[PDB]
Each structure stands twice: as structure tokens, then as C-alpha cells.
Amino acid sequence: GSSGSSGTKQLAAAFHEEFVVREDLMGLAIGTHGSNIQQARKVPGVTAIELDEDTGTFRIYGESADAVKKARGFLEFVEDFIQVPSGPSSG
């Protein structure tokens, strides 16, 4: 995800993604201290990224579907995963 943006050709976004995520999966979908989201916004072609809590619908804005799509994967819901550190290092 090398950096090197310039700007937006059109004010609005030609492509827009709008989907509803389970309020139960949202948490994980977003990650810690807004990790996922932050990342999704770090994706090129993405003009902006809004989220609706009232219903829980993630609204992505990108000049090209390819962008909003790549970022969407980050906002997409994720099944409950359990990854153990297999060795809690104290220090």
C-alpha cells in the first residue's frame, strides 16, 4: 500500500458501497481503537468513509468501486476468532 496520492478528480465518488453489519460483528469488524476503519480510510480511491450507528450501515465513498471494495473488506464483518499467544511473555 505504498503512499503517493494526489487528490480527487471529482468532488463526489462515482462508486459508493452501502451495507449493513451485525451490531455483534461490528465490534470486531472495526477492531481495536478503530483499527480496521482507520485502515480502510488509508486505502486509495476512497474519498470518504461514513458509518451509521442508528442502523449499523457502513457507507463507503470511492471514485472507483475497486477502491471502496478493497477498503470494504476491512469494514466487513469477521467471525469470532480465537488466537492464543501460545506463550505469554511477561518480560
Image (cartoon, rainbow, N blue to C red):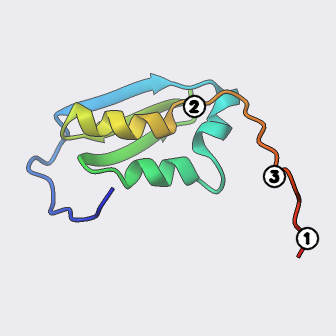
Q: Quadrant of residue 50?
A: top left
73 or 9, which lies in front? Answer: 73
| Residue drawn at x 73%, y 34% as measured from the top left | 81
Question: 26 left or right of 49?
Answer: right
Residue 33: percent from left, percent from top: 64, 57
Is 75 placed above or below 55 here?
below
Say few, some or many: other residues with alpha carbon within 10 Å of mark 2 (under 14 / 14 to 19 / 20 or more).
few
Q: Which mark is residue 90?
A: 1
| Whole-number angstrom distance, CA of label 2 to CA of label 3 | 36 Å
Point out the image quarter for the N terminus. bottom left
Q: Which mark is residue 54?
A: 2
| Residue drawn at x 59%, y 37% as measured from the top left | 29
Question: Seen from this angle, which residue lies furthest bottom?
Answer: 91
Residue 12: percent from left, percent from top: 18, 42
Question: 24 left or right of 18?
Answer: right
The amino acid sitting under disc 1 is: Ser
Is 69 placed above or below 4 here?
above
Residue 70: percent from left, percent from top: 35, 38
Say few, some or many: other residues with alpha carbon within 10 Å of mark 3 (under 14 / 14 to 19 / 20 or more).
few
Q: Which residue in the protein does label 3 denote?
A: 85
Q: Earlier in the sequence, mark 2 or mark 3?
A: 2
Question: 42 left or right of 5?
Answer: right
Residue 11: percent from left, percent from top: 14, 48
| Whole-number angstrom distance, CA of label 2 to CA of label 1 | 41 Å
The amino acid sitting under disc 2 is: Asp
Q: Nearer the viewer, mark 2 or mark 3?
A: 3
| Whole-number angstrom distance, CA of label 3 to CA of label 1 | 12 Å
**Local SS, label 3:** loop
**Local SS, label 2:** loop
Q: Earlier in the sequence, mark 3 or mark 1?
A: 3
**Local SS, label 1:** loop
